[PDB]
Amino acid sequence: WKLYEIKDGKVIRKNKFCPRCGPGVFMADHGDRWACGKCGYTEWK
Amino acid sequence: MAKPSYVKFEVPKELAEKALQAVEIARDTGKIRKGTNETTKAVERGQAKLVIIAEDVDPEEIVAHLPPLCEEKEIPYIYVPSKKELGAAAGIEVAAASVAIIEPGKARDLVEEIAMKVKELMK
Amino acid sequence: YNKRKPRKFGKGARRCIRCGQYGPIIRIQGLMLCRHCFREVAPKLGFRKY
Amino acid sequence: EFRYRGYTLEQLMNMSLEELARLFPARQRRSLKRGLTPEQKKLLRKIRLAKKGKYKKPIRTHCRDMIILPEMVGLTIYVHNGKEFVPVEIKPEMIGHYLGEFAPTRKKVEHGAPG
RNA sequence: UUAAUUGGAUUCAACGCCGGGAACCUCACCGGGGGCGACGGCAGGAUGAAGGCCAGGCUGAAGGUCUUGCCGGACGCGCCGAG
């Protein structure tokens, strides 16, 4: 719930959605990379 | 006792009892998501078919996001007066502030009814 | 981490069926038995002293 | 100067591992031919990074059968003999011999009065 | 003597004996590190793992350890009896 903000009628997500498992998958916001903690898949920024 | 800000309609007592019955039957022969981050994930995932929310939740933020997000995703929502009642209907000792049903199971006939009684509440 | 390494070779690759000793294990046609265990099992195995 | 099969330290360094192993004994060349374990490659990466300067940690190790290569010359590493990681330093003359030869696994055996 | 040459075996009736095969193992010896106490009572519980996850400093070394950022959805930390 903390990662979910709401502004003017839309839900903002702090972390991004890992595309392998679909939505609902928050994954590492490391600043330099978007890493997923479930399998180690890393999409560098 | 004024209703909190996230309230958009008044749920009668019989409708709250029916919602708790639906929660119990979905716990028995279906699937419910205890906890509010899981409910948010379900509503985002679209698996949530009805979001039951407690009215006496001391922190407003946990339940504040549910009404506008549910209305955005066209997933009906209902209220129950006590988070303790929602937790007891959830089969867990600790209080569950929000429960999103995924498979009503044998509660569908109630849930589809309750959803109907939800659809008249916003009008 | 809590698993012993597989061993297809050496003495450690053979641990007797009955007594579990890691040392003498005769495998003639695959008995897979310890030497000290063979005395209780030989006569029932059709072995006959001649 | 240092000599090994007609090549000095840098003359050994500039060449790949194939002839570099052809200069090594059978027990070393053949083992290099059959490849290195997952922890030998990791330690090689560690020491290459340290020589570059990236890995600033004092490097300890346990791989006793690690064959010293000329690339490891000029570095200090701590090798395990069973109790502690004894320090050793790699000079150009260490080429062609295992690391586990360089740690006393048995302390000196002296003699006291008989029973 | 060692950290270790593990220990047993005492003349016949101990000493090519256990070992009828020690480079990991064998290990019963030493140094170092990691991990779970089953099933209960007390306690937490869905309030979100206890399983793993990259970049790395300690780790021989491994998300073991920790800064880092998180899910997988669920009963699992811990003291006593008892394992």
Image (cartoon, coloured by chain):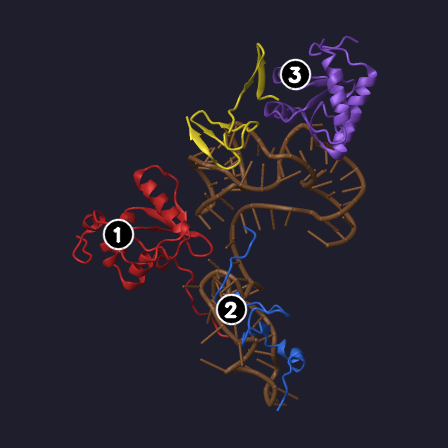
Chain colours: A yellow, B purple, C blue, D red, E brown
**Between marks 2 and 3, how big is the CA–CA gap?**
65 Å
Between disc 2 and disc 3, the foreground one is 3
For residue D29, the mark is: none
Please name the residue that numbered disc 1 is placed on: D17
Q: Which mark is residue B61?
A: 3
Q: What's the chain of the residue with tag 2?
A: C
* Most distant residue in the bottom direction: C50
Looking at the image, can residue B89 be seen? yes
Classed neighbour count for the residue bearing mark 2: other residues with Cα under 10 Å, few (<14), some (14–19), many (≥20): few
Q: Chain of mark 3?
A: B
Residue found 66% across the figure and 24% down from its top: B36
Percent of width and height locating residue B38? 64, 27
Q: Name the residue located 22 percent from the left edge and 55 percent from the top edge.
A: D19
Q: Could you classify mark 3 by the number of other residues whose Cα lies within 10 Å: few (under 14), some (14-19), or many (20 or more)? A: few
Crowd rating for badge 1 (residues with CA inside 10 Å; few <14, some 14–19, many 20+):
some
Q: Are marks 3 and 1 on the same chain?
A: no
Q: Eyeballing the image, is C39 above or below B17? A: below
Labels 3, 1: front one:
3
At which x and y percent is residue E19? Answer: 52, 76
User: As rendered, which of D19 and D78 lies closer to the eye?
Assistant: D19
Q: Does residue B17 appear to the left or right of C16 in the view shown?
A: right
Quarter residue D101 falls in = bottom left
**D29 or A17: nearer the viewer:** A17
Q: Quadrant of the N terminus of chain A?
A: top right
One can see residue B84 in this view: no
Q: Amino acid at mark 3?
A: Glu
**Pointer 2 residue:** C11
Tell me if D84 is positioned left or right of B71 in this view: left
Please tell me whether residue B54 is drawn above or below residue B123 in the rendered image: below
Distance from disc 3 to disc 1, alpha carbons, whole Å, reads 64 Å
